[PDB]
Length: 448
Image 1 (cartoon, helix red, strand yellow):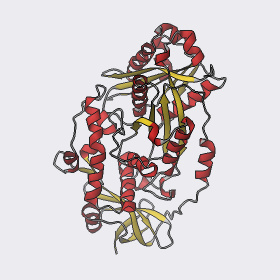
Image 2 (image 1 turned 120 degrees about the vertical axis):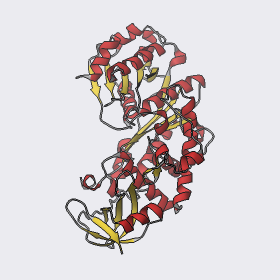
Image 3 (image 1 turned 120 degrees about the horizontal axis):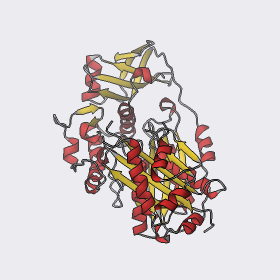
Image 4 (image 1 turned 90 degrees about the vertical axis):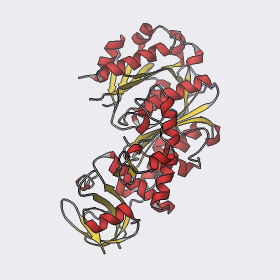
């Protein structure tokens, strides 16, 4: 190795009401202890703290652990951020920038798409998920089975994870069967498949030179062997609403950087608030959904607990532990990412190497050069349903549609028409003809 090469040396998790500072503090204290050196000496050596977004929250965490770092960072929103952050400080440790960095996050118990209803995460993921159902040509009930078969192995791992907050294990049948208890929320998801905790996570990272200076046992060092960060264009510009090629590209580029192939990976933690971003990696990569290696280390999002923002740092922590236990093997972490907007991948191993710079910037500019699908904001005429969702938590039930015209440009529409909503809830709408009427609040729709 080169002395500037970055290693993860300490990881920390905590579950418990404590403040969000207090929770990140508890996890940070465990990261400092995990490294096997004197915590206080390590704390004095920290030059940067970075926190994920939930006052100076990163400096309060620092004061609490005995650190006085020159830089404090408050990162941008999104589930990609823990892994984006680890990659960014890896790179800066590799150059002449930083030497000891602490990353942490926590959570407490306490445009033209906006005006159409796309405000929360679930309704928007519904559209992507129904778009993937279109491309695969699966029926509604068939797809619902696929989702339950993907997620049941998740909740099993989740139930044996002590860091999981109040988890019950669920069978495939239990997830797929609509009851008064497991009722339809947003199409196509039943309640048990989408669902508040106290938890903190921290990562301690260093140059190999700082690890020796500070007295950190070598059996604790883990390398970030591969990495990539990718980004999609806004939802209605995407070539296929049912896929995210940027996520797959990130995975493949991170694989290249490590010098390995998909078969060489021993363990996966794939980000899973909804089935889609998991499915999507599987579709573009060849990885089977029932792969014996497993697709989660943590148990995943519905089941593990949490809002979604700081989830992947628990992933990274589990990856790092699992890799110390199986020295020489490789672990992939995937972090999502808005409305499948962002994806960040890290591959971890005890096997040493020099930091390899990734090709994300040039891969991003290639994907940015792809043609964008055209949008008609004020659509007036006859169109085809490309994808849809329904809000079952509203009365009357409310449909959101992305459509196509004859022109081939996309639009959005909202609908409470009793006739149309019956087709979206109880049948198979893809491709059905509808008539859309413009309006500056929402475009409305009805059958043809």
